[PDB]
Image (cartoon, rainbow, N blue to C red):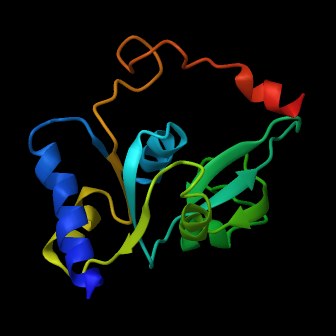
Amino acid sequence: NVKFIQEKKLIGRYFDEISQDTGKYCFGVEDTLKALEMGAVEILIVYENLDIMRYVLHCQGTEEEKILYLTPEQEKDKSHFTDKETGQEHELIESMPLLEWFANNYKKFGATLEIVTDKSQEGSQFVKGFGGIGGILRYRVDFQGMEYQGGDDEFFDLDDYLEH
């Protein structure tokens, strides 16, 4: 019956600690993913019915790939992946379930992928905080990026290093 306490204890800690502004938690795929790449997330709390997945969009001129988080509505528009109101530039090639992805790479990130639900009070908080994805950090971190963002590695060209 860990599921009952899994949501009440793990999840509650997420908001309770944040109640101290300890800066050891995050909400949302983008945020939760960022800290999970940072291995700064002690325990990852995600939901089964997550309406967010990892997709790979192309560019109008090509030679450039974009990765964004979409919902059934947006994902449904795979061919265009654009908007008839703005005419963005998106072209879906592949689509990987973020939940499944978080449950298959929880070791690489060192995070603990725990799948919760809005059934409990705490489970109701995550939905309010964001709605599907939240992360618990191992310890107080300053994150990496610009001056306000934190560090100074926001512009890491190391991404191209992988390709080489």
Corner quadrant of residue 147: top left
Q: Position of residue 23 (x, y in %)?
A: 24, 35
Q: Quadrant of the N terminus?
A: bottom left
Residue 90, above or below 163: below
Q: Position of residue 97 (x, y in %)?
A: 62, 69
Q: How many numbered marks appear?
A: 0
Q: Quadrant of the C terminus?
A: top right
Q: Tell me what residue is drawn at x 38 percent, y 66 percent.
A: 132
Say whether residue 16 is visible: yes
Q: Tell me what residue is drawn at x 17 percent, y 72 percent.
A: 8
Does residue 143 appear left or right of residue 86 in this picture? left
Corner quadrant of residue 140: top left
**Residue placed farthest to the bottom in the image?**
1
Corner quadrant of residue 2: bottom left
Q: Position of residue 136 (x, y in %)?
A: 32, 50
Q: Tell me what residue is drawn at x 44 percent, y 79 percent.
A: 49
Q: Position of residue 108 (x, y in %)?
A: 60, 50
Does residue 138 appear left or right of residue 76 in this picture? left
Towards the viewer: 140 or 54: 140
Towards the viewer: 74 or 134: 134
Say whether residue 125 is visible: no
Towards the viewer: 105 or 118: 105
